[PDB]
Image 1 (tube, rainbow over the protein chains, first blue to last red):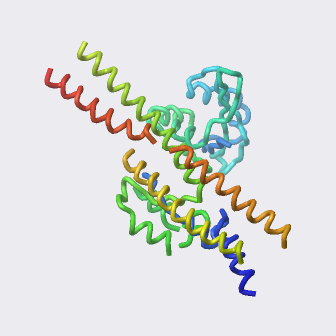
Image 2 (cartoon, each protein chain N blue to C red):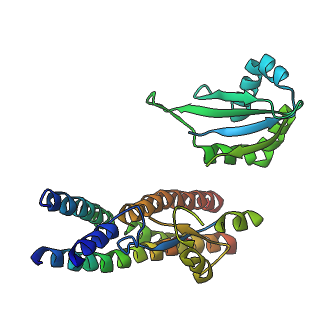
Image 3 (cartoon, helix red, strand yellow):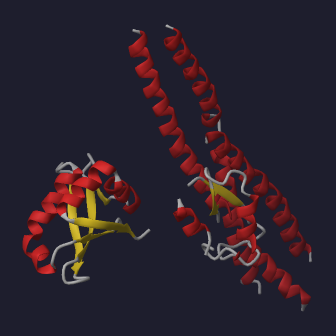
Length: 205
Length: 33
Length: 50
C-alpha cells in the first residue's frame, strides 16, 4: 500500500533521529562528568606515592576553598617518565547540594595563563577535556548524524565565519535549547553592562 | 483518509511555524552578538 | 492498527506540546538589552567628555 509509507514518512518527519526530520532542519550559527586528563612529567610510582600531596596542590590551584574537592578518576603511565592523571572536581552549593564541575568550565580555568603556569610548576605538561586551526579542526569531518552536503552548505552559507561556526541544531526542544542559553546569556549581558555602569558612576561621582 | 489528511496539513502548518520561530531565535541571537 | 493511531497521534501531539512550550517561552528581555547598551555607551561619553 502507498498508504503505509506516507504514514512512515510522517512518523519519520516527527522525530530526533533525522530521516528528513519532519523537515525540522534548521541550522543556527554558534560563534567560536567533568573529567579532565592531565599529563605529568613524572613517573607513575612517584605520582601515586605523593598523590595525597598532589591532590591538595591541585586543590590549592583552584583556590583551596572547602567547597571544591578534587577527585582522582585514575592514573596511568604513558611513558616511563610521563603519567596521565584524570581528575574531576566536585563543587558544593550553599544549600549543601553537590555536583561535578563541568569539564569545559574546568578546562577553561586550567588553560588560563596564570593557572597554566602554576599547573606547569606542578609538572603538568598537557591537559585535555573529553567533551585558529582548531575551528578547521572541528567544522569539518561532520557532526551529530547531520548530512555531510547540508553541513557543507551551512559552512558556505555562513554569514560571519569568525564570529561563527556552524552548529547543528536538533526540532523544538532544541530551539528550547537555544532559548535557555539565550536567557543564560541575557542575564550575564545585563550584568556586565551593570558592572560598566557601576564603574562609570564611580568615576562620575 | 479523513485522518491522514489531518496529519500533513498539521505537519506543514507547524513546520511553516517552526521555521519562522527558529528564525526568531536566530535573529535574537543575532541581536545578541 | 488502531492501537496504533492511539500512539502516533499521541507522540506527535506530545511534540506539539513542546512546540507550545517554546511558544510560551518568547522576548522582551532581549529587546531590553540594545536599549541599555545604547544607553550605557552614552553615559560613558559623558564621563569621557567630563
